[PDB]
Amino acid sequence: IDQQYVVDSQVRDTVQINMDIYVNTKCDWLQINVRDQTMDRKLVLEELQLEEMPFFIPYDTKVNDINEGEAIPAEFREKLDTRSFAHLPEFNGCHVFGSIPVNRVSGELQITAKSRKAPLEELKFNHVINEFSFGDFYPYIDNPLDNTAQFNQDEPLTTYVYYTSVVPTLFKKLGAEVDTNQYSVNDYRYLYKDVADKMPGIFFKYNFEPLSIVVS
């Protein structure tokens, strides 16, 4: 097995963004938007499920603002109920998950407060990314943001921005019909005082590289 760079001929027009995230805010305060070069902000309503949860950071999850044994405050381990398989505002949470078809062009997925705006007290953008991927899942996949979390109990209104650069791949062991992609990422954070982008939140910027990696 060897991998080679080739010209991204046959550029697909669209790609699915797959997401499974916990946000430390109740669902009904949240809005999720997509925008790209071609279009103005489109509200993502029907493509995602938003479900109330007690916010928690799962095990086997990188806790990725180490700077600001165990970094998870034991307060934020998973709460259970008899039918798992009403809390402190510390545990306000929303499980956001689904797959969104977007144009395969430079764009951005935004999770922010609905905005005459959510009481800051209620807003906390601590989050856990269980999945964030592009295209069809495949056995070799290794997404940088999967199983990661950011939290800061002292900075709830922190804005997190991820810049993801997406590379389409052809694994000859899988076929060309499967929409396989991998990405690299660089990360930014902004304190609320600086942001006061005018509304804070969690932002995934994405662009698609004009090459492919062929795996033979």
Image (cartoon, rainbow, N blue to C red):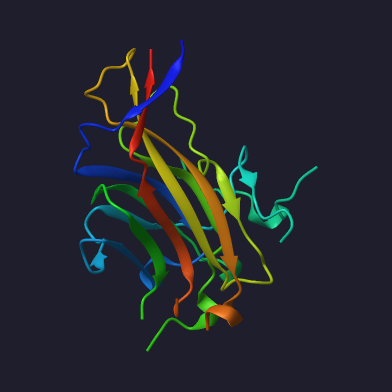
Q: Residue at position x 21%, y 57% from top?
A: 46
Return the x and y of residue 19 as percentages of the image width and height. Answer: 38, 47
The residue at 52%/40% (across/down) is 144
Left or right: 126, with 134 as reference point: right
Please give the name of the residue rendered at 31% of the width and 47% of the height, measured from the top-left corner: 98
Q: Position of residue 23 (x, y in %)?
A: 49, 60
Q: Residue at x 51, y 47 (%)?
A: 185
- Front position in the image: 151 or 57: 151
Residue that extends furthest to the right in the rendered view of this protein: 69
State whether residue 107 is above or below residue 213.
below
> Can you say whether 198 is above or below 127 in the image?
below
Outermost front residue: 7
Can you say whether 205 is above or below 62 in the image? below
Could you tell me if residue 141 is visible in this image?
yes
Q: Looking at the picture, how far across and down is residue 95, in whole percent?
A: 42, 54
76 and 176: which is toward the camera: 176
Q: Quadrant of residue 113?
A: bottom left
Report the label total: 0
